[PDB]
């Protein structure tokens, strides 16, 4: 799994389940092209977004729909989404885990990058 | 101050000085219109971005050039930038402080929203 | 200010007001000796904890009563308290700002250390 | 696994490997009794600290030796350790994952609490 996203809920102390996210890749004309999308599982994880062959060098954006998550819990949050923009694979293939820890007015995000 | 941004360095335990950022506002066609910009002071703060009259309801994006900050310290960071996307002023004017705490592979952000 | 503590609420997007904390200093027998205390102001800040002359080399512990803060909001939090343990003044006086960003099941803390 | 701890490195974008930690439980006389200890694996995880039978209701403290971790990388960090103090199992048995995201002058920590 070259790209995995894990989302945690800092209010409830749980994985953030059924969180939608969209991945984009910067095109040659500097526009954001749709790349992949999905929803987190009961473990707060989204696996299977891409493959080694498809996940080429580039600038990628993961846009996590935190707003819908909070609104479904009756909370009016601050952010429209949490987004993570990064260059991937520019020194050869790597495995990326993007983690996001969510609160209504705050988020933290980190990356774990491993060389297979 | 209708909109202030404060940036902190989690590696050195200091304000993040001379950090550049642009602020955009979403246009009716979903493109990002230039709205404000600047760089952080020696206190890690950027004041004077906008005025109360100009800062009306909209979706705003603060795009913080964290990559240039880390590169100046000889550190190859994960993110291209840190971005904070939020609706502002939908219930009339508020004062917004956006804080960002930076590490090479991670950032945390929070908002303090106060009614004038 | 030799030692200041700032506390933020990640659920409500506000300073964390009226948050109680005690500061201890490690004694020669490894017990924690009372050193300072107070509660945060309407700005979420606690100033005036110590003076430069009294604040010498030692291991200090700031114990922030986050549990009482969340319980006052009807929220059952995870932590008994947030604690920040650090050596201070080992290279002579410095000014320390300890910031804590609170959620019910999570907290983040950072330090800003400045040379007078 | 009733208690698991996961530690991540925000500077290097990696699991925090070989991080020592000590777990204590508050005794009837309000002292901290040694409860368990171990070191994180190559995945940054420490499993097997305790068992369902041993992990009774109580106040627990996880003290993560972040100082030695940073010093081994040539970094003089701010904190002596990162500590997590919490009541466990007071409504019946739960499974706890404690996560900590480490930087030299900052740490974030969260808990995921699940009912088996
Ligand atoms: O506490 C810490 C930890 C750590 O990993 C690095 C530093 C200092 C970094 C640094 C790099 C380049 C430069 O021109 C100046 C600097 O201070 C301080
Ligand atoms: O943006 C958010 C999110 C969220 O989950 C809760 C709040 C407000 C909480 C609250 C609770 C008790 C009280 O007396 C006052 C309060 O404001 C605001
Ligand atoms: O651990 C963390 C995470 C994070 O996202 C922010 C902070 C501190 C933010 C901050 C905001 C306003 C202000 O006047 C001062 C501040 O330090 C601390
Ligand atoms: O306090 C924080 C802040 C933050 O941004 C992330 C975490 C947890 C991240 C995480 C990453 C990979 C994984 O397999 C599991 C995880 O829990 C904890
Ligand atoms: Na290359
Ligand atoms: Na409105
Ligand atoms: Na010294
Ligand atoms: Na009980």
Image (cartoon, coloured by chain):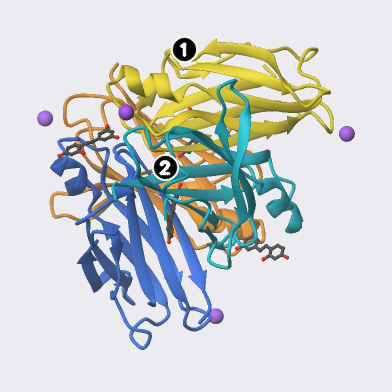
Chain colours: A orange, B blue, C cyan, D yellow
> Based on the displayed image, in which of its 4 quarters is residue A77 positioned?
bottom right
Residue A30 visible here: yes
Q: Position of residue C9 (x, y in %)?
A: 57, 57
Label 2 CB less than 8 angstroms from ligand 4: yes
User: Can you say whether A103 is above or below D39 in the image?
Assistant: below
User: Can you say whether C97 is above or below D92 in the image?
Assistant: below
Q: Secondary structure at mark 2?
A: strand
Q: Position of residue A43 (x, y in %)?
A: 59, 32
Label count reads: 2
Residue hosting label 2: A109
Quadrant (top left, top right, bottom left, bottom right) of the N terminus of chain C: bottom left
Q: Chain of mark 2?
A: A
| Residue at the spot 54% in from the left edge and 46% down from the top edge | A19
Q: Position of residue A57 (x, y in %)?
A: 19, 34
Give the left or right position of residue A86, taking residue D94 as reference.
Answer: left
Q: Secondary structure at mark 1?
A: loop
Disc 2 from disc 1: Cα separation? 22 Å
Residue hosting label 1: D41
Check whether the beta carbons of the residues at disc 2 and disc 1 lie within 8 A of each other: no
Q: Position of residue A74 (x, y in %)?
A: 67, 61
The residue lying toward the viewer, choosing from B53 and D36, is: D36
At label 1, counting other C-alpha atoms closer than 10 Å, the crowd grade (few under 14, some 14-19, many 20 or more) is some
């Amino acid at each position: 799994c070259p790209l995995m996203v894990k989302v945690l809920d800092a209010v409830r102390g749980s994985p953030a389940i059924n969180v939608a996210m969209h991945v984009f890749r910067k095109a040659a004309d500097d526009t954001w092209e749709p790349f992949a999308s999905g929803k987190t599982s009961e473990s707060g994880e989204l696996h299977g977004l891409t493959t080694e062959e498809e996940f080429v060098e580039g600038i990628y954006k993961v846009e996590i729909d935190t707003k819908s998550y909070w609104k479904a819990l009756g909370i009016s949050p601050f952010h429209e989404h949490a987004e993570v923009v990064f260059t991937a694979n520019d020194s050869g293939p790597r495995r990326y885990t993007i983690a996001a820890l969510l609160s209504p007015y705050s988020y933290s995000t980190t990356a774990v990058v491993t060389n297979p």
